[PDB]
Length: 27
Length: 248
Image (cartoon, rainbow over all chains, first blue to last red; front, side, top):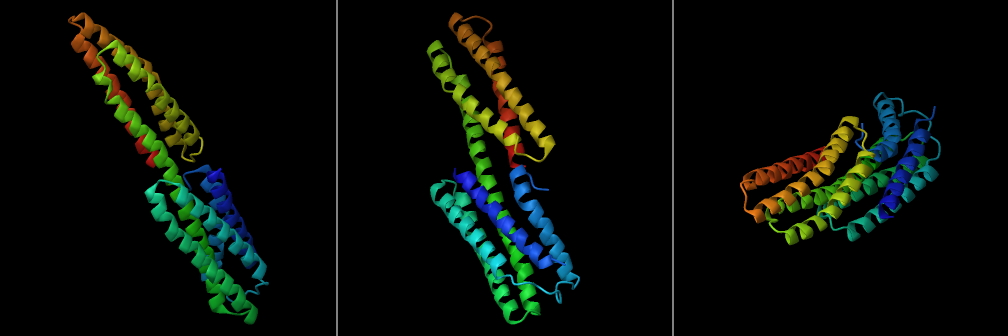
């Protein structure tokens, strides 16, 4: 559905940003 | 922190990671920290942002909610402009690994992605809530018509087109309360819905008596009117309470 597609898209943005922030922060 | 289980599960871990990065940046730790090649991790963010805007655009066009149509495009600009800074920061860091402006772009970009994604989820959620409130208000308006019912034929017509609206509202409240993170508001919604559900047969029974007293032309009319109006009043107060809690 359109709701599931929208939510899954937002989740993908959060996940990719989290992976980027973790890569920047990395000690 | 977030009012919905879905919004909390999506945003909370990325918000905490950014808050931690912001702290390190303002403390001066990020400035001279060696940063690996970010071309691929940033490309993965740009690909995800493009898909969110595309899916967001599909919602804007197919929806009828004018507030969602108005509020989604400024958030699309926000996530895209944030993506711009991340793409550019990755380029700047390849030419100068010690670039201080590029590190500032990484923080502003990550914050912008979070802020825009948060705006989009909150706008989408508020539109889903407005759908439920529309159903609630339709029932409220329909309850204002109970006093017009004065014959058996009116009673059959009235009851028939009340039953589905009530079933639709109950299903929407049940699904919504299960999504809420604020447990006290979940209790308020379910209890208000229980009251409305249980008062529906009380209203139908009061309308039946009203029709019978009116037809017999007996001394029980004023009490029948008062019992019907009081049930409409209590149900209406409870539906208005549901609308209020849904918006909190």
